[PDB]
Every structure is written in C-alpha cells, then in structure tokens.
Image 1 (cartoon, each protein chain N blue to C red):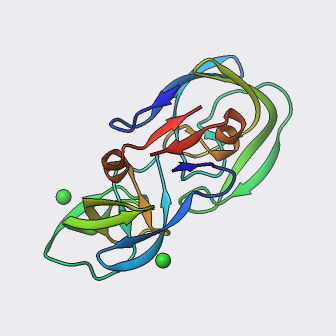
Image 2 (cartoon, rainbow over the protein chains, first blue to last red):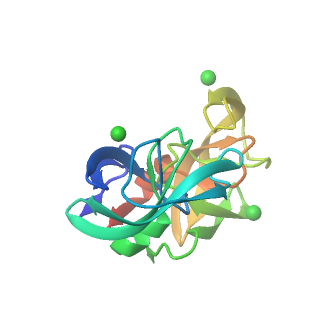
Length: 99
Length: 99
Ligand SMILES: [Cl-]
Ligand SMILES: [Cl-]
Ligand SMILES: [Cl-]
C-alpha cells in the first residue's frame, strides 16, 4: 500500500497473533512495543531508543502481519510511549519513502 | 526520489541558507533542528520531544531545499538529539510510505 502522511501513520497490525496499533516510524532503527506477551524465547538487551537507555526483552522470529504483508521479525518489548514499527521491519516489507 | 531504509534516511538539505544533515522521520509530527540561527522572527512553543516537554523556538515561513525540491515551512529550533524533517515538511513534498 501507499501510506499518506497527513495523519500519523498508525496502522492496526497483528503481532504474535494479537492486534495492536503501531506507528510506522522511519526515524526508529528497531521495532519496540509496550508490554505484551510474544511467543517463544527472549533475551534482555539494552537499547538507546529513544529517551535514555532502556532494558528491553528481545524476541526473534516473530510473525507480524502488516497491511496484508507477512514478515518474520525481531521485536523489542519494553518502555516506549508508542508501539513503533521501525526500519528493521520496514526493510523486510520493502518499504520506501517516495516523493 | 525513492529513499530506502537499510540505513537511517539522513539527507543533506538547505535550510534558511545553511546546509545541514537531517533525518526523514515519519514518527515526528514537526520539523525540529538543533540550535541554528534561522531567518526572521520566532515565537516560543512547548512540544513533547521527549526529552519530556521542551521549550522551542517556532519559526514560520522558512525556506527548505530538499533533493532539488523547494518548500516554505515552519521549523522548530530546540534540543533534539538529531535534526528531524517531520510530517509537516514531508506532506508539502508529497512524501508517502510505499510497500
Ligand atoms: Cl495497541
Ligand atoms: Cl548538520
Ligand atoms: Cl505552546
């Protein structure tokens, strides 16, 4: 699809089988969601996204469906004021900014 | 142009007569640069560049040249860890996200 930027680009996606809102954030290197359960194993990680260092849980191999497309991705769970889809997933999606 | 997201989408732009690096950030409502002296007058504004709430200088009608395109825009000057082109500018350029 083609997402306009008149509004915040917040879409409903299905992440690890659950429906969530998230913003497509080209300023974000990684994908980070607020506390929720994801399937499988995780490892703790320190990241700098995006207001101080934070400890997050990193889950690899997470199925995400976004606007009809399915990817398998690394997702961080921790303190974030918004759920954020970042460039790691956007690259997997083939997403570009076009003008 | 078509900007891919394998790396941070940082571009060199011309803003108020100066060349600056900035990141194309679909997660940012507004366009904010670090301390710079822009042309014209400004008014104080609070914004949630978190950061917590930060006081910024708001400049209106600032010319911006980005990849050969010229726009006249509102720019915030204040604390920000990077110079950010946000959606206000992107919409003026006709930017979309596409996958
Ligand atoms: Cl949600
Ligand atoms: Cl710069
Ligand atoms: Cl204000």
